[PDB]
Length: 67
Image (cartoon, rainbow, N blue to C red):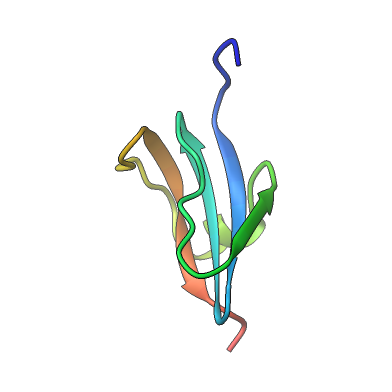
């Protein structure tokens, strides 16, 4: 789409939650779905960044539910 900057997707799993801001890629699903979301206050609140994504470079982290 005329090239777009970084973007984050909040994925959902039967018992997990992932926050990722890619850089030329998309949200890789595994056992649930995902939604559109610029970034995440918790992503930075616990991780930091990323980069290694099959189709592109990303930046963010992953973690279980609230438990």
